[PDB]
Image (cartoon, grey):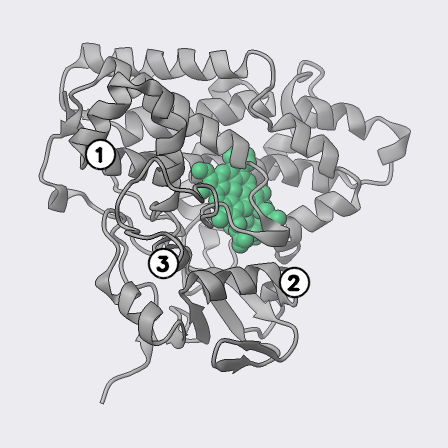
Amino acid sequence: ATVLLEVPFSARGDRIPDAVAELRTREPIRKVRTITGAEAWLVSSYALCTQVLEDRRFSMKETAAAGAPRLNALTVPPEVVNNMGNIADAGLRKAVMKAITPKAPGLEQFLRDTANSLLDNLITEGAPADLRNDFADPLATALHCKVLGIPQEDGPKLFRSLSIAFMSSADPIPAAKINWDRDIEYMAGILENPNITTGLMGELSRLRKDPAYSHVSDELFATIGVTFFGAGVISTGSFLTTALISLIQRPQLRNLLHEKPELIPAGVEELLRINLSFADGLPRLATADIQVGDVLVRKGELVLVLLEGANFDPEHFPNPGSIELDRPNPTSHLAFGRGQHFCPGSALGRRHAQIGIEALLKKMPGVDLAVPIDQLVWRTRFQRRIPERLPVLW
Ligand code: HEM
Ligand SMILES: O=C1N[C@@H](Cc2ccc(O)cc2)C(=O)N[C@H]1Cc1ccc(O)cc1
């Protein structure tokens, strides 16, 4: 006799566990136990994952209710789980959307210059180089400093919170509140800084003084900057890191994109589809009794949407483990979510990876792992799957 199935199955981000395909075929919605001891429904087929994400009766906001079954402990104040809803209710949705588009002036040129500059420094240091710590994460940090309008020099200060902020823990984390309060104070001070006139924070600083927004709290302005820095940097840094592994593992594809850089957008979209950067299913709480497949999910129960369950579903993406640049439904993957909470930084995340991969293949076309792939150290109890170091030669 053995306990219920425990999630997550594996912290490894370079291969999908064989357990996923067996669940999807036999039990596409199945009861599991989370690290807090709570029971939850895990949803692993394309059809059921999309149904859950498009039905607003499965609520993100309500996962923060006291006494709800939990996937993990909150590392933010409970109101911040409703971050996007708080933004829209204060009338700030359009303003935030336009600050994070990759079409901001000089932003693509900044991304390319910063990428090339990071790679030159790696080249002059000599091999081996760490493509996570000395390329992907700094490129992500620099990009979000620029998007936010804050000094590049403050990037590493704010990045320091992220190894704790995005932890996937069974219990509350004392350090997370310390860093949160300190980071909120930093962004509050940015709003009072007359030199901050560009980017998201520059725009928020001027809306703050506009009569149409005089009843929006200073707390919310500062929260927008912390949350968008944190979610954007950890999501873009982690995706680009694990996308470089899938590329290194496929030298034919690596060579094709080097000779034909026009295929990089199509390649990045497949790298998004097969990416394993999210370490847990997306949590939602049922606010009603709702039929999902063969199971009646009851009000108050937790449902977990497994992104790789949908994205590797052979009924929607035939030969799902293969990168194919000519699929007829290329953007229909769930790497950015779906429905109400679709990622607002999808365009920016796509552009970060395209420019990073393009710069890498032009400077480092023979890039390869400097250690056997089994030697990578995968971070555990974290909301993203990432190797601690990514040593490469070229
Ligand atoms: C490759 C990069 C990225 C990936 C794979 C990614 C993935 C995702 C996914 C799957 C969700 C939905 C979560 C859910 O429904 O529970 C989401 C939401 C979100 N993302 Fe992204 N994201 C990326 C980049 C970004 C960037 C660049 C930003 C901002 C600078 C950002 C900010 C947000 C925010 C604030 C939400 C919450 C949206 C809401 O609650 O309505 N993300 N992301
Ligand atoms: O809880 C939230 N918190 C912030 C994201 C966030 C989480 C932790 C943190 O330290 C900073 C930001 C939000 O914008 N919305 C929600 C939902 C969310 C959670 C994780 C994630 O990766 C994206 C969205």
Amino acid bearing label 2: Arg
Amino acid bearing label 1: Leu
Amino acid bearing label 3: Asp
Q: Nearer the viewer, residue 191 or 382?
A: 382
- Residue 178 seen in the current view: no
Location of the N terminus (image quadrant): bottom left
Q: Quadrant of residue 139?
A: top left
Q: Nearer the viewer, mark 1 or mark 3?
A: 3
Residue 56: image tag: 2
Label 1 sits on a secondary structure element that is: loop
Residue 390: image tag: 1
Label whose residue precedes the other's in the sequence (2 or 1): 2
Q: Residue at x 44, y 27 (%)?
A: 352
The image position of residue 121, as x and y in percent, is 27, 12
The image position of residue 277, as x and y in percent, is 36, 46
Label 3 sits on a secondary structure element that is: loop
Q: Nearer the viewer, mark 3 or mark 2?
A: 3
